[PDB]
Image (tube, rainbow, N blue to C red; front, side, top):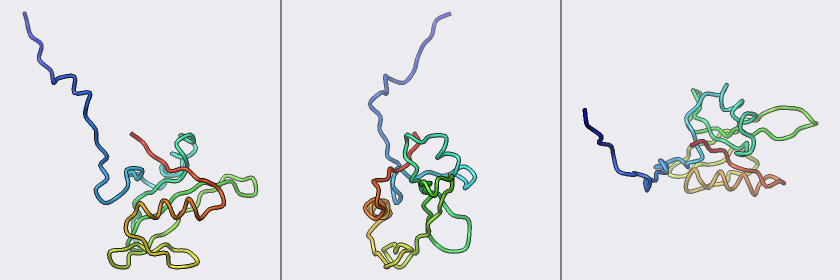
Length: 118
């Protein structure tokens, strides 16, 4: 017997899979989007998950310290044209999903961190 053929080192391959949505984003269910936070805290808590129904857009799951309790919040994002308005005090117009992630960072009084999973 004699054989042995496999793809080259193929160690120089990279991918961002961020066509319309930011890499940070991930496809998961609420039940998960929540735990995923407590599970991988070092990887920030700010993550984005695809909604189910109701309106058009994506939500932002963020678990911040409140009155010393464990609670997560899910923000909503409106879809008005080629831009995505943020559901907040003022209708902050952006150019892409990425912006939102940022606006939130500067918005909060604390430097939050995005969530990612390779």
